[PDB]
Length: 121
Picture (tube, rainbow, N blue to C red):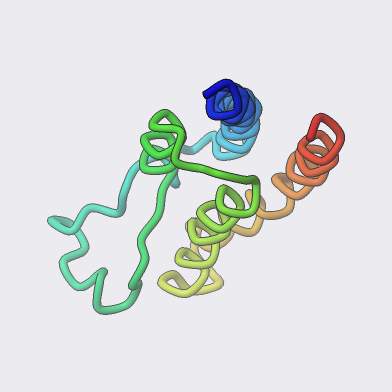
């Protein structure tokens, strides 16, 4: 139908916007701490601690499959990156500290994203 197409164009444009959001958030991680999944070869107990692992490469795969229906779903995955890190790693670690800085700096980007998503519909 024409409606299904219109809907598909909306999703494509959301995907376009979320791709720009993702790039902006990932720039706030210049150390690439959150770029890839925690390695289960190198941290073999990880899934005993963290039940829903997440990382920027995994978000990108979902994004490019158009698997984010709305900004909330995208934000859920970003929050998992941060929250998983802040539980697994102690406060006095470069990992924890990187998550805090990513959360703080990401907030600005996500605040405008939500306005843009609502604005453009």
